[PDB]
Length: 13
Length: 326
Ligand SMILES: Nc1ncnc2c1ncn2[C@@H]1O[C@H](COP(=O)(O)OP(=O)(O)O)[C@@H](O)[C@H]1O
Ligand SMILES: [Mn+2]
Ligand SMILES: [Mn+2]
Ligand SMILES: [Mn+2]
Image 1 (cartoon, rainbow over the protein chains, first blue to last red):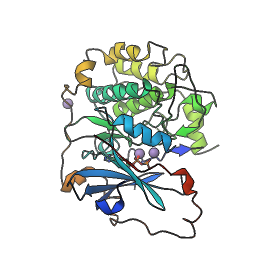
Image 2: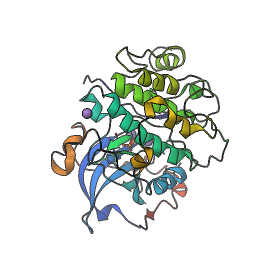
Image 3: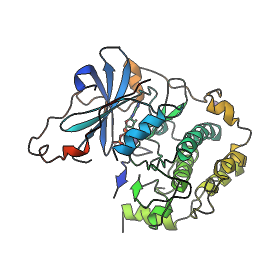
């Protein structure tokens, strides 16, 4: 898919 | 304690890096909720539960109904916000007027302050984690990065958050406080009004990390002088110079800024301001306000692997069972 805003997952390290 | 046998599985409404969110119904009392399903192979637990507890007594926070667990998963029964999230309602709108962004960020600011003044650092403010209700207001969900126990003047060092929203303080390996939530609100407000992340338009995620640290935020010429100044004051790379990061005078500074002037914060806290956008609750339970990549997945739970689930140290989830007593 191609969209203006992309779903980003949170990171923890 | 409640259980999976007491809930009706309706639809899959969300997915993240830690959990799968399902639309559920308590079979006994016909009430409609959302259920955050967290697998224990990824997995805090003291913090995310206790933060859902606090959030239940606030208008702009998602509240906790009950907690229960299975051999493979952890379940969070929370409220159901049937208008979707800001991300969904931003890929359609593509860009918001400053009057609209001011409304959402003001309500977020109040919710954030309530967390800040209780010792909690949200540390994951993004489009996905803000939801629109049936009337047009907002609610904050997903407290996976939340910190707990911040007595006045404390700092933490955990590298966490969403890659686009991580504050420079974290990127510089510094200790940080609530300052990281007002940076994310800055990045969020930039997305609402400009229509694009201020960092998107060693080489792909660490490229963003250097951009976030070295690149300059370029406000488009179509924005107002008050909007420009509220972004430059929230996206200030120096936490000691940022808006809202003013010891004792933090929230007051955010309420006194030209952008957040002419705004009534006490009517806003009391849900007396009229939303600029009222969600179009279409479909069953308002499911046309959620992406079809999730509402088309089969409504079920993924089968278990007795070889993978036999490694989980279940002596860390002892007191997870919980039922909110009103
Ligand atoms: N109470 C809720 N009501 C409606 N939608 C929700 C609710 N909680 C989560 N969601 C949806 O689920 C998605 C991901 O859930 P989230 O709690 O962020 O899990 P993760 O921590 O895995 O990202 C969000 O983008 C949001 O749209
Ligand atoms: Mn989320
Ligand atoms: Mn999370
Ligand atoms: Mn309007």
